[PDB]
Length: 144
Length: 142
Length: 139
Image (cartoon, rainbow over all chains, first blue to last red; front, side, top):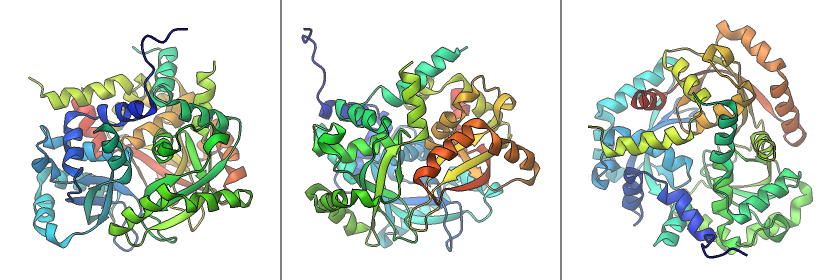
C-alpha cells in the first residue's frame, strides 16, 4: 500500500488538464467570458455565405478588454479555446457592430484573410458572437 | 534529434497520459470493440449541422464510468484527442438514446444553448474508438 | 527579450510537437503542397466531419515514421496549423498512390463497417496562417 501522496480526484484532473494548461492569455480570455459577456467574432469560412463549408480562422478584439499580453496570437488562442470546447460561436450581435468594424480593419486579420483567399477563393467572413460554452462554464465552476 | 521510440512515446503521452480513471475505462471498453449511445447537439439544423456544441452518453457502469457528472467533459476530451468517432444511429441502442434524451444534465445544456442558438439540433449517434485511438492503444500496449 | 506569453506558447508546442511534425511544418512553410485524402461522413444529416486523413508527404517532408502520418495530420489540423484546399490536378498520381496504401485502405475498411455512406475527398495540404505564425515563433 502506498497512498501518502494522493492520486487526484477526477475534478482536479479535469481542471488541471483543461484550465491550468491554458496559457495566461488564454486564461484571461476565458475569465473575460466567464460572467456571460459576449464579444465580436469574425469567422473565416472556406466557402461563401451561400455554402459556408468549414471554419478556417477566427479573430476577435476580446483580447483588448481581457488584458492579454500578446494580441498578435488571438487567432491561435481562439483555435485552442474552440478545439478544447471551452467557447462557442453564435450569430451576429447588432450591438457589437463597431467592434466587428474594428476587427475587420485589423491589419493582421486582413493578412490572414488574404493568405487564405489564395487557395480558398470563395472564403467568406462571417460576423459571429464569442461566448463561453456549457463545458467551459462547468469547468470554471469546478475550478472556483 | 528526436528518435522514433521518443516520437512514439511522445504520441502516446500527448494523447493518453491525462485520462481520468473513468476515461481510461471507457476507452478500454471502446478498444474491445464496444459501442455506446451518443447524443450530440449541433449548432445548426439537420441539413446544415454546423458545429458540435455538446455530447452526452449514458455509457455509465457498462463503460466503467463512476462519475456520470463529467460525461460531457470526458467525451469532449476524447474527441479532441482524436480517440473516438461518432458513427450513425444504431437501432439496437434505441432504449439508450431514450435514456440520454431524458437526462437532466443533457436537457439543461440544451436549454442553455438554445438561448443563443435557436436552430440547434440533436443527432442520435454511436460512440466507437477511432482508427487513431486503435493505433494509439496498440502503441501504448507495446 | 521574448515576451512571457510567447514563451508559454512556444513551450507548449516544444513539449508536444514531434520531430516529424516539425519537419512537416517546415516543408509546408516553404509553400509546398501535398496530396491529402480525407475520409468523412457521407450522411446528409451529419456535419460530414473528418474521420481520417492521409498523405504521402513522406520523405518529401522528411518524415522518418510514415506509420504515424494520420496521427500527425490529426494534430496539425486540430491545432489549426494547416488547411485542406481543393484537389490539385498536378497531384493526381499522388492521390492514386495514397488511395492504394495499406494504412489508408485499412482505416477505410474499418470505418466503412460502421459508416456505410463513408466518403472520400481528395484535397491539398498546405500551411495555414496559424502554422506560419507558430513556425516563425518556434524558429
